[PDB]
Length: 108
Ligand SMILES: [Ca+2]
Ligand SMILES: [Ca+2]
Image 1 (tube, protein in one colour):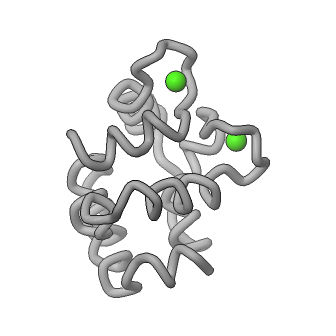
Image 2: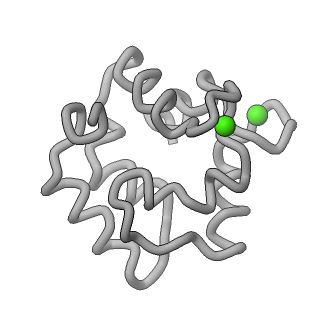
């Protein structure tokens, strides 16, 4: 998909392995290559993470973030999910919008 076209599978594997002892978004975004992608590439990624095309990554989607990169990956636990949301959700609506996703990828 766009994921495996935009990102290198080997980088995805690194980022997934890094999750074994706990998910940290900055480490994941670095390993995966997300923090090197352009504005426009990040919007494309956002659209495929937004499974229901709501315009947002809701918390229920965010729990399944790793599965967007590999379907067999684990779910995030509640601590992981809440910290990730907290990092991204600057406008206070408890979901991640396209602008917030770009900002989280490049400026954290
Ligand atoms: Ca959504
Ligand atoms: Ca938000």
